[PDB]
Image (cartoon, rainbow, N blue to C red):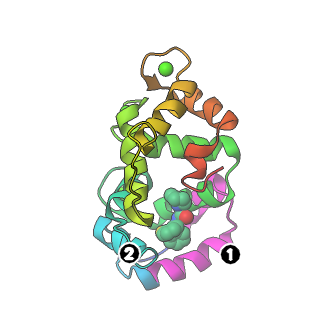
Amino acid sequence: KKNSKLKQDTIDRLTTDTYFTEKEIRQWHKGFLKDCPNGLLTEQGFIKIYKQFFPDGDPSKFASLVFRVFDENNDGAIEFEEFIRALSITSRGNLDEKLHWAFRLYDVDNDGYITREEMYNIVDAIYQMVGQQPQTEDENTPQKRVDKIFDQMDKNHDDRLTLEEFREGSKADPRMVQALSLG
Ligand SMILES: O=C(CN1CCCCC1)NN1c2ccccc2Sc2ccccc21
Ligand SMILES: [Ca+2]
Ligand SMILES: [Ca+2]
Ligand SMILES: [Ca+2]
């Protein structure tokens, strides 16, 4: 296809932008096409991949949130180049890069701020995936513990987190990014 072949121009950009060698990129492409012969990974295809890893819960919500960050050009598919860029950051990136990636995940509406509600959303999604837990203390729910973490990161108390607040906030309390395995 136009999307099934790995073109040199794609490799050039990927070796410029990522932590992968040309050899690794070519190897990854073989694996990408095995899982995705069309060269394009759909949202539901992405969800199915997560269901293989968390058969107990429902990883649908979390996978959809992650999908949007992989799909950086917002055309509704993950192409190989997008897959590799995201893999590079999340598996080989430095702390600042990983934190920025996590910020993009939490900023669901891409308005440049994380709200409490956005943070609730991701946390809920994670619990749906790995297993929800009953709380008998209304003062000690996930939302309330998140509120405390949020409040501590929200340095000017405007009820929203900038990238700088989240990134610096997470270096002192890495729990929101460790929750994505990015700390
Ligand atoms: O590990 C990531 C990126 N994750 C890390 C933290 C959660 C949010 C971003 N990619 N990924 C991944 C990780 C876990 C489950 C499914 C996937 S699909 C996939 C297919 C081939 C190689 C890597 C990946
Ligand atoms: Ca895309
Ligand atoms: Ca937002
Ligand atoms: Ca703020």
- Name the residue: 44% across, 73% down: 54
- Name the residue: 40% across, 50% down: 135
Q: Can residue 11 be found in the magenta stretch?
A: yes
Neighbour class for label 1 at 10 Å: few (<14), some, many (≥20)?
A: few
Q: Can residue 99 be found in the magenta stretch?
A: no
Residue 112: image x %, image y %? 43, 30
Which residue is label 2 attached to? 51
Could you tell me what secondary structure mostly forms the magenta stretch?
Answer: helix
Which residue is label 1 attached to? 23
Q: Amino acid at mark 2?
A: Lys
Q: Picture quarter containing residue 129?
A: bottom left
Q: In the displayed structure, would residue 137 be above or below residue 61?
A: above
Determine if the C-beta at disc 1 is less than 8 A from ligand 1: no
Residue 175: image x %, image y %? 60, 45
- Helix, strand or loop under label 1: helix
Q: Picture quarter containing residue 13?
A: bottom right
Toward the viewer: 144 or 169? 144
Q: In the displayed structure, would residue 92 be above or below residue 159?
A: below
Residue 144: image x %, image y %? 44, 36
Using the rendered image of the protein, determine whether residue 84 is visible from the camera's viewpoint.
no
Alpha carbons under labels 1 and 2: distance apart? 30 Å
- Helix, strand or loop under label 2: helix
- First to last magenta residue range: 8-33
